[PDB]
Length: 395
Ligand code: HEM
Ligand SMILES: CC[C@H]1OC(=O)[C@H](C)C(=O)[C@@H](C)[C@@H](O[C@@H]2O[C@H](C)C[C@H](N(C)C)[C@H]2O)[C@@H](C)C[C@@H](C)C(=O)/C=C/[C@H]1C
Image (tube, rainbow, N blue to C red):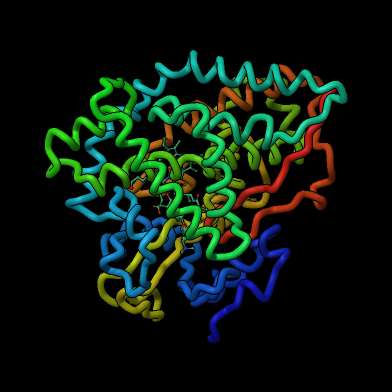
């Protein structure tokens, strides 16, 4: 079959990619596409095959296994655990695994609660009882939490929304590359500013680790670590909060059920992940050798994107897939991935989303979507499922 041009859609395809993916899945697990940006990649669709490929060591994450060239700015940031295989992956993840356990993350709850409380305070001061939920809460919450953990100073934080807007939806490819070079330059200076300062934030601890033994964490890896810990959880958590609140406000029966029984909160957040999680397609995977998927052979070195969004709409795995049901059995969803790269941030993301969702329901009487669903606009990006704005209102 010819390469499917996703740009030529659709539209449209950004607003509702699901029928496109489903049509592909009916034909088989693996498809050549051209993304709206213009890149020729493979999509893997269908829950069982997506789950298998996420964890299959035949599919590498190390760019040395890719035939796609990297720009200088891109290459400077790729020595990180998500863009590594064992043994490098194993070594890098061990340096920070203890910081992100459920137990350690649970210690942040009072502070996360305080941040949320103050953002909702500020939101509810609006004299017209209207806000954009992105601006008021979904954007500032995750950046505040992760900045405090890592040690990014408050005046430095606004620059990250500008850079992430550029990575997500860039005026042209060159502004994404400038954003990258700037962010890398900034992080290197931030890292340098910690040296000798006896800071106790995570970035300071990583700097001492690297300085004490460059074989345990090299200077490139120190920069890649600050980068991945900041970027991997940013656009994702922001959009979990926004997509999830959208799901709730556009399914009032479910909103009412959760209001009526707040013990349903954790399962509601799991169904937000399943139903409309922020990661539409996983990060790039590169076969180390050719891989046959049901008669379709993907060449060594090609780019493969696992379509988590389609996995989650596979009816054999999640019956009545297009129903948002906060009581659904969500076990096995792929929203945080699967296998050795499974999200290290999952406990922190869940903590943030659960506290945010609870705060909004509890403190916004008659909370409502303030435009019709058809008026919302989704960013076109093939990796991220995320809204431009989320107008809400309350009483
Ligand atoms: C709801 C929010 C989040 C979602 C949906 C999410 C999703 C994911 C997914 C799908 C992967 C695997 C990607 C792949 O295999 O190609 C991943 C990995 C990762 N995530 Fe998360 N993430 C979220 C929040 C966070 C946060 C808050 C942090 C950091 C504090 C974080 C840090 C990371 C890191 C460092 C990796 C790479 C792990 C590894 O390679 O071993 N994420 N995430
Ligand atoms: C949960 C994983 C997050 O993605 C990542 O952590 C990876 C490492 C990542 O940073 C890349 C996917 C970024 O994408 C690349 O960005 C460059 C500017 C250009 C490059 N090119 C091929 C288009 C592009 O793939 C990432 C900054 C993309 C944005 C949307 C993002 O924030 C993703 C976050 C998670 C999906």
